[PDB]
Amino acid sequence: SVVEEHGQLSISNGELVNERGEQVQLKGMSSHGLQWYGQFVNYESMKWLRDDWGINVFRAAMYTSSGGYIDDPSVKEKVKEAVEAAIDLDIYVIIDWHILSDNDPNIYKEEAKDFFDEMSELYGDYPNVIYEIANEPNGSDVTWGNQIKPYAEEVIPIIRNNDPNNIIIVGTGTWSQDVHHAADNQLADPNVMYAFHFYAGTHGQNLRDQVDYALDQGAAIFVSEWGTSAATGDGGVFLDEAQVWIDFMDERNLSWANWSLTHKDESSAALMPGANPTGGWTEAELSPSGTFVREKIRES
Ligand SMILES: OC[C@H]1O[C@@H](O[C@H]2[C@H](O)CNO[C@@H]2CO)[C@H](O)[C@@H](O)[C@@H]1O
């Protein structure tokens, strides 16, 4: 129903809109690393998230390093499983080239270009797909102008040769927080968005003001990852600040995916140890984070 109704997504005046020009807000879940917690990514779990939580997007977080794709490329097949499930379930899907320790997206740029060539060749005639080409550029030696923008200007053409207008999300500096610099030096492609990531354990008032600055330059922002935890993915749950961010995102038409769908013993994990990898979770099988996130999506 979601993808049939909204169809082709695009950016209009810095906003994500559907094929009839109406603003649309995506809200869903990210997997954790597919090399570690891939069992939670399947048609049945995604159907349960769609039906019971109300998700309309799913993010497939394919780590490149940390035992991910570069080390063992078999994980690309799990991305394919996820995309196919989203197509079957009529929801949107984010294909995330999930850089992190490999902090400069240029490190694996050749591999990224080949990967996105393949993905866009396979799926480029479906409206479900959103390409996230570099999760979290980070480090003082990785800047928008010198590293990230030129990387994007190599990878985007590869995608566009197969898929001329599905959305592409481009990571920003400082673990996808530096939307200010991106917004002042935007990419040419009209269907690009810049990633912004937050963790509720960080006091967020200036970060919200920076997102507003970026929006005011006409840049579109996708909150492609956020957590209820501290920035590590752990360290307690911060639901008061998470709610402030939720309300902020609603007011600003910002789409989002929550980190993450796993049973790992960390505060950001949505599931308890014991949760069935194919869905059907009772309230006792959701963590405090998962309970909150599910409520936010159901409310929406
Ligand atoms: O892989 C290191 C670490 O990653 C955390 O997840 C991060 C994600 O990869 C990028 N955005 O920030 C989040 C939080 O730091 C996981 O939560 C950890 O379990 C994992 O060890």
Image (cartoon, rainbow, N blue to C red):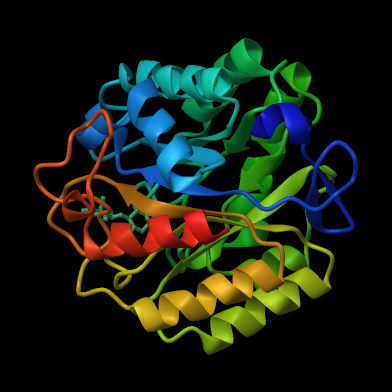
Q: Position of residue 209 (x, y in %)?
A: 65, 84
Residue 9 sits in which quadrant? top right
Q: Is residue 35 left or right of residue 16?
A: left
Residue extending furthest left? Answer: 274
Q: Quadrant of the C terminus?
A: bottom right
Which residue is located at x 47 percent, y 76 percent?
Answer: 243
Q: Position of residue 223 (x, y in %)?
A: 56, 58
> Vertically, is 297 above or below 49?
below
> Vertically, is 180 above or below 29?
below
Q: Is residue 83 visible?
A: yes
Which residue is located at x 69 percent, y 19 percent?
Answer: 126
Q: Quadrant of the N terminus?
A: top right
Which residue is located at x 52 percent, y 44 percent?
Answer: 134
Residue 185 sits in which quadrant? bottom right
Asked whether 185 or 280 is in front, the reply is: 280
Q: Is residue 174 left or right of residue 160?
A: left
